[PDB]
Image 1 (spheres, rainbow, N blue to C red):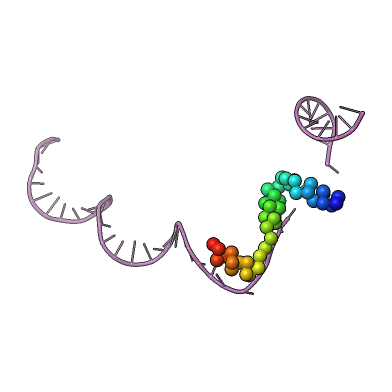
Image 2 (image 1 turned 120 degrees about the horizontal axis):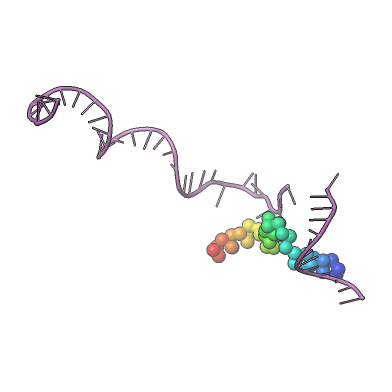
Amino acid sequence: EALRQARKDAELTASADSVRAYLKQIGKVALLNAEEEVELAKRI
DNA sequence: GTATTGACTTAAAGTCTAACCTATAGGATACTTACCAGGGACACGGCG
């Protein structure tokens, strides 16, 4: 509950440091596995 | 001294050929979030 509000408040922060901001934005998307890779490549 | 021609050799190109740089591509086990001051003035967010 309070932890949830804390996490949300955190997500709305700049962190100034541009490396820090990019390192934050790259973690949004999860990784994949082999079958996901092959289906994705087939789509491409 | 100042008017010439006929050779006689020479550096500077002008060019063809060869090697030595240069722009570029590629590489398939798997690896997935880096790292001691003060002193004054002005502006922004909270609280009453």
